[PDB]
Structure formats: structure tokens, C-alpha cells
Amino acid sequence: DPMVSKGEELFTGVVPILVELDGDVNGHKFSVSGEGEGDATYGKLTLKFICTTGKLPVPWPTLVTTFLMCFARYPDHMKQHDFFKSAMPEGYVQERTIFFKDDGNYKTRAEVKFEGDTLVNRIELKGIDFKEDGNILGHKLEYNYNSHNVYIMADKQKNGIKVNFKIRHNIEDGSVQLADHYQQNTPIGDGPVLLPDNHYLSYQSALSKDPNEKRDHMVLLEFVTAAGIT
């Protein structure tokens, strides 16, 4: 399939990844740069994020979804459902609103595209209506991450896809902080793109630290596989 092959060819190997985020949460201004590589053949990503403005004013875990769906492993039997690679190299806009229960919300707009051999994820994030002493600005979340599937649906009107999913961030008392995700993606380019039938991506995420790193940071190892059309 010559259409589907174009975007596929870009992901057959290990691809360098650049992430840039510019953020403001309740007037806490911060920037994060991230680097690593992704191997979509295996749905694998390896990333390290640095807060370049000092201390991250929010928990790392809350930014994990915001910090690369083109790196999912879509099985062969599902290749006609891979919107994300089909939009490449011209890329796609990923937009979200993320509602933290009993707290504030994040609004994000990201451009995911190739710049030569590097896959770039450029993000702006605005956070509003957060409680200073809430779980987010008060840093009350565990430094870990639960496995979640995420349900991709076609969004014909936007030449694109939508996603809604809920993340549960474990708290230091057995409580969970919910983060209700609404997401839309649309091509940057004008060309044909795949419009999938409903399916989902399964995510597993592990967070760690680098002993040699003195800046505030997050090491992220992720695996992501498409499923749900049998």
C-alpha cells in the first residue's frame, strides 16, 4: 500500500526524538527539553526530560501524556489504521485538555513532525484554576505510572482522530488523582491520511531518574502497541 508505505518507511529503524515544552501553570512559567529515540517496529521509546528553568512546578507524572503516538507498534493486520505515521513527515497537530478532578486543567497544543531525521514534538501548555496546595502544585503524586489503554477514534470532520481516556495518578495515601484527557489530532499537511476505525493503543510507562543528573528531570521508558480490531 503506497500511501501507507510512505509514513511507515520513516519509522522502520531507530529514530532520534526531540521534545520541547513551554509551559505556564497558574503563572508558574517553566520549560522542559526532552531527548531520546523511538523504535516503532517494537513500540518502544526511551526519553529523558529536563526542566531547564529549575524546579518543575508540577509533578513529572502529570506531563507524561503531553511529552508521540507515531511511535506505536501497529501490527501488520492493523497498518491501515495508523493515522499518526500516515500524517508523516509533514506531521500532525495534537491538542488536549486535561481535567484534573477537583483541581485545575491543562490545555496543550503540540506540533509533531520531522525535521530531517529527528522526530520533533513541540508543545505549548497552559494550566489554569489550579489549587496552590492541591495535588499538582503541591506535588502530592507518587513518582510512578499506571498502564492505560487509550481509545482512538476517527474524527472525519477534522480530517483526523479524537481520543478520550482517563489517567489515574496514585497518591501517597492510597487515593488516586484523576486526569481526564480529551484529545484531537489533525494533519499539518494537505495530503491523504488514514482515517482509522475505532481501536486502542496500550501504554506502559516507567519513570526513573539519572544518578548523574543534578537538574530536575525524568527518565521515561515506554512501550505502546495498537489493538482492539481483532
Image (cartoon, rainbow, N blue to C red):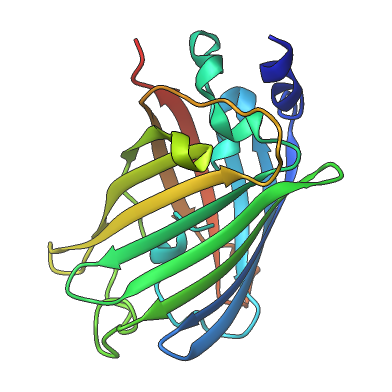
Left of 140 or right of it: where is 34? right
Residue 145: image location, x then y, percent = 35, 52
227 or 152: nearer the viewer: 152
Which quadrant of the view contains residue 214? bottom right
Q: Position of residue 73 (x, y in %)?
A: 54, 25
As drawn, which residue projects farthest toward the left? 174
User: How many numbered marks have been drawn onto this rendered protein structure?
Assistant: 0
Q: Quadrant of the N terminus?
A: top right
> In this orientation, which residue lies closer to the viewer: 209 or 46?
46
Percent across and percent down for residue 84 are 58, 35
> For this rendering, which residue is in front, 68 or 3?
3
Q: Is residue 142 visible?
A: no
The reply to whether residue 89 is in sight is yes
**Quarter that holds the C terminus:** top left
In this view, the residue in front, 171 or 18, is: 18
Residue beneath the point at 65% across and 68% down? 212
- On screen, residue 172 versus residue 71, left or right, reads left
In the image, residue 58 lies at what x, y percent?
Answer: 41, 77
Residue at image location 39% in from the left, 70% down from the top:
106
Q: Residue at x 38, y 62 (%)?
A: 97
Q: Is residue 68 above or below residue 53?
A: above
The residue under the point 45% across, 82% down is 57
* Extreme-front residue of the structure: 157
Q: Residue furthest right?
A: 116
